[PDB]
Amino acid sequence: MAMDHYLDIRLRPDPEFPPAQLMSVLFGKLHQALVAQGGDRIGVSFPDLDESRSRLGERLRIHASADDLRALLARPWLEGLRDHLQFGEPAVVPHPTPYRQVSRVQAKSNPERLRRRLMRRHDLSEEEARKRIPDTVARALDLPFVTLRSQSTGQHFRLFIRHGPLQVTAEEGGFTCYGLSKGGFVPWF
RNA sequence: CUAAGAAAUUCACGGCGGGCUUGAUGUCCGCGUCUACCUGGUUCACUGCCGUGUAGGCAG
C-alpha cells in the first residue's frame, strides 16, 4: 500500500555461482553496505518471488524511500560485484498496493539450544532437553524462507524472514537497519 | 466339479584295538598402457544467551 519508491534487482544466470548463491551474495552486500551507517527506510521483498515451488529467492525487488535510495546505492559495499547482476531503476507507486508486510526476523530452529538456555539461565534438565529433539520437534519455516548464511556454521540456511498476508489491505511498519519491516512493509506488485 | 473321499503308525542302544609313506629334482626367454576432466556433493530441506509456550540485533 505504501510502495511508492520501487526498484528491482535481477541477478543474471551464469555458471560462476548459483541463483541462491547470487541472491545470498546480493543480500549480504546490501546488509553490509546499506545498514552500515544505519538508516530507517529499507524494504526488500521478493520482487520475483514464488513461495509454492519451495524456492525462496530467485529475483530481488526493493521498495524503499527516495532519499534512502539516493544515498543507499552509491558505496563500495554495494558496487564491485555488478558483473553478475545489474543496477536498478525507479518506479512510482500505483493505486494497487497489497499489504505484504515483509520483515527481516528469525524463527525457531534450535534442537538443543533449549538445553544450553537451561544450563545457562534456566536450571533445567539438560539431558531431557538434549534427548527431546525429534524430527517433529523443530518448527521452522517450511516454505521458501531463504537464509543467506555465512561461512561460520556448517548447518544449511533455514528460514529467516517476516512475511505477511497478501491481500487487498494495507499494512506498513518500521524498517530496521538491515532492510526489513518491524510491523509491516511497503507494497508488492 | 480339484485321480473325489481318509489314516498316532513305535519304544532301547559302548564301535574298538594297532601301525615309519620314503627317496631325487634348473621354470625359462621378451615386452610403450595412453588420451581428457568444475566435486558449489546441502557431507541432517541445521547447530545457538532472553520464558526450557513458534516470545531477540552477529564476519550464521
Image (cartoon, coloured by chain):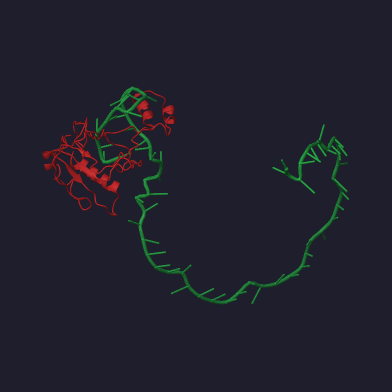
**Which quadrant: the C terminus of chain A?**
top left
Residues B60 and A27: in front is A27
Residues A98 and A182: in front is A98
> Image quadrant of residue A131?
top left
B13 in relation to A22, above or below: above
User: Image point 25% across, 45% down: which residue?
Assistant: A59
Residue B34, image x and y in percent? Answer: 42, 69
In the rendered view, does B45 fall on the left or right side of A168? right
Residue A68, image x and y in percent? Answer: 13, 39
In the rendered view, does B2 fall on the left or right side of A118? right
- Residue A118 visible? The answer is yes
Find chain A in the image and tell me its colour: red
Residue B42, image x and y in percent? Answer: 36, 46
Residues B3 and A89: in front is B3
Chain that the image shows in green: B
Residues A90 and B52: in front is A90
Residue A144, image x and y in percent? Answer: 31, 40
**Which quadrant: the N terminus of chain A?**
top left
User: Image point 44% across, 28% down: which residue?
Assistant: A127
- Residue A71 visible? The answer is no
User: Image point 29% across, 48% down: which residue?
Assistant: A19
